[PDB]
Amino acid sequence: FPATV
Amino acid sequence: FPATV
Amino acid sequence: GAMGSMERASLIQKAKLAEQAERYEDMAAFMKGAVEKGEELSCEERNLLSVAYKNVVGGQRAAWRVLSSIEQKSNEEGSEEKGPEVREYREKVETELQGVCDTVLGLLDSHLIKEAGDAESRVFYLKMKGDYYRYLAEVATGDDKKRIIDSARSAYQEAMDISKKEMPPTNPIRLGLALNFSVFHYEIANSPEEAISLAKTTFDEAMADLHTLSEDSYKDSTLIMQLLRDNLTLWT
Amino acid sequence: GAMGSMERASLIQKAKLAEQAERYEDMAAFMKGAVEKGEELSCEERNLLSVAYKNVVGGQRAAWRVLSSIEQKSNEEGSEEKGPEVREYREKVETELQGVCDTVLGLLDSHLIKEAGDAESRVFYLKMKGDYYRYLAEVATGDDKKRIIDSARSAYQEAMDISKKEMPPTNPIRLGLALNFSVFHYEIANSPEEAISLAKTTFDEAMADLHTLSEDSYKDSTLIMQLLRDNLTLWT
Ligand SMILES: [Ca+2]
Ligand SMILES: [Ca+2]
Ligand SMILES: [Ca+2]
Ligand SMILES: [Ca+2]
Ligand SMILES: [Ca+2]
Ligand SMILES: [Ca+2]
Ligand SMILES: [Ca+2]
Ligand SMILES: [Ca+2]
Ligand SMILES: [Cl-]
Ligand SMILES: [Cl-]
């Protein structure tokens, strides 16, 4: 999965 | 801590 | 409210303890109680709220994905019939996840967003609104799915508009909003080119402003920039 | 019972799904429901029960230790008074932990132990009884603390007596029982020499019986033997 914050 | 199972 | 009898300051203190103990459900319940006191949240308090629910929903999302994968495999040709249990349990986890998202959205709507006038607070909460609608969109399959996606988009877009007008391109909230909205484009809106364009433009505009920053601010902004780069690398 | 309307087989299936999803609270609730159906548990089912509650209580114990450490530091000379919140929250976690232990002990007493006649099942459940009384002893400070410790000791001792009579020295249940009883001696009963003697004797008697085992059994027994060795290394 891609990075989120 | 010591090992337990 | 179960936390109605506890002091605001005590709820904040206990949220911090819960964080240290990795008790994120408790952390989230304490922060819900703190929000329900009715006063605005400081920067630190907004961060506690976001961290608590991020960890709770993150665990739910991970579980949902495991169960969804099992369910998908069960519906493949040559798969032996095992009854309704996989679907039932995936549905259980999904319903709990939706409940957490609804709770967060409820806090934002009653009344965090409407009382947030400073750009930093308003953008922070609108980012959260986008994020939790995004999580609802991840599991949506029915007739409101388009409306859920549009709710996420609308919240992110309002946050983006404010951030571009009011915050420098290196601001961490602005950067993190852009990172997440870019993921929304890629994973939810089926718009990978928009996702890539947003990540690239965000990265490049931040790079050009780093010269203005202290060592400490530089560290924070470059860490988030690296996440944009990581996503770009994944997508190209 | 919230699980009263669900089939036994469905509860077992869902416990396995919950395990895969790392949803240990759900796993434990499913297995409680399965036990409450009233039928004996197979080997695999006993293991699901034990794994579920081990993970739930293990998380509680880790949190309790974090909070206890903070509380200890708050009561040191020169520590600024921060109010009742640390104690209150440690107490909250402690009460939840005690509740989980009481639930497990209740399942064992109603009626898993009394219906377990084979040595393997009876020893497995008596080990669990010792373990959950040990967890209660970790947090006990009042007038029943001695009685809690003695309850752990008594359950472990009955399990040891059966295991020595009925099981080979390499049997994994026998080995794991000895490992845990040795930890009880070291950490709870203030008997480090007994702990060391038990671990050493257990290790040595298992070593001498390895020649009787298949490759697969050898692997299982040697893995547990290494845990005995690890504890001995820690203690000597
Ligand atoms: Ca009140
Ligand atoms: Ca007050
Ligand atoms: Ca559903
Ligand atoms: Ca305001
Ligand atoms: Ca029933
Ligand atoms: Ca039935
Ligand atoms: Ca207590
Ligand atoms: Ca029986
Ligand atoms: Cl279910
Ligand atoms: Cl509390």
Image (cartoon, coloured by chain):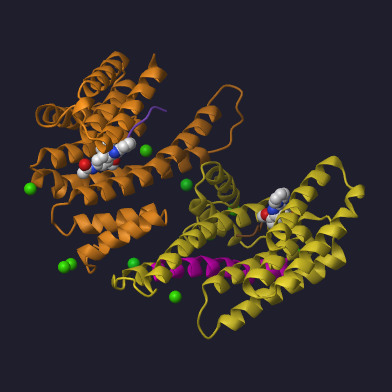
Chain colours: A purple, B brown, C orange, D yellow
Camera-side residue of D92 and C221? C221
Q: Which stretch is magenta? A: D90-116
Q: In which of the image's four quarters is ligand 2 placed?
A: bottom left
Residue C1 seen by the camera: yes
Q: Quadrant of residue C211?
A: top left
Camera-side residue of C1 and C174? C174
- The quarter of the rendered structure image containing the N terminus of chain C is bottom left
Camera-side residue of C70 and C162? C162
Residue C63 location, x and y as percent?
A: 46, 40
Dominant secondary structure of the magenta stretch?
helix
Residue D140 location, x and y as percent?
A: 52, 76
Residue at 62% over, 57% down:
D50
Residue D168 seen by the camera: no
**Residue C33 in the figure: left or right of residue C76:** left
Name the outermost residue toward the bottom.
D143
Residue at 50% over, 55% down:
D5
Above or below, D48 against C225 in this view is: below
- The quarter of the rendered structure image containing the C terminus of chain C is top left
Camera-side residue of C206 and D57? C206
**Residue D152 in the figure: left or right of residue C139:** right
Q: Quadrant of residue C170?
A: top left
Q: Is residue C171 magenta?
A: no
Above or below, C83 against C30 in this view is: above
Above or below, D16 against D144 in this view is: above
**Residue D120 in the figure: left or right of residue C106:** right
